[PDB]
Image (cartoon, rainbow, N blue to C red; front, side, top):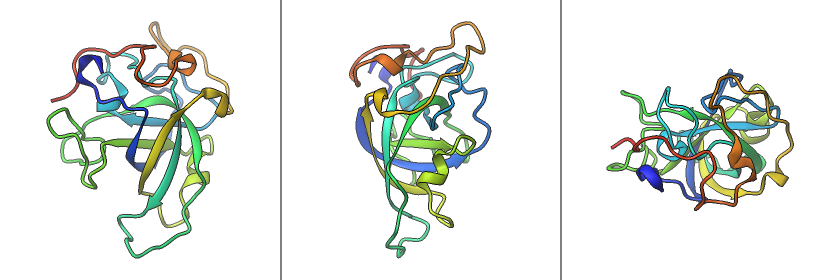
Length: 180
């Protein structure tokens, strides 16, 4: 996409959970299930505002625990999240570290969704004892997402992806150039 960000409506991802999603990188939280997406897909860098992932809705399905590879299941439910947040590329950390020159994480996954625990998404998705998974995602209409957006936390906050057709398309827009 614009800026060299890797923004595909479907693909393979790693999945984790996190706490404290009330002041996320898009600048609005939401009451439904939400996630952070890896920087290369988010469409912005820390401190640069919303990227084009903001507000888009995705169905997530976990189907492998790479940390317990002999575990056959069961996995969780398929859930629909709204992206409100950024999982940034960080040093000494493989998760979310996808870049334009090296587009996969330690599991070979080109995307990451960090599912917020606060509002219930991670409890639907991760079996007890299996809090990091790999699997698939597909962008869906936000008609498939229960929830209400929170208020703007700063000028420029954006979840406009929530009414956009699936990628390829532009709503909030990407900021600058993707990490190399």
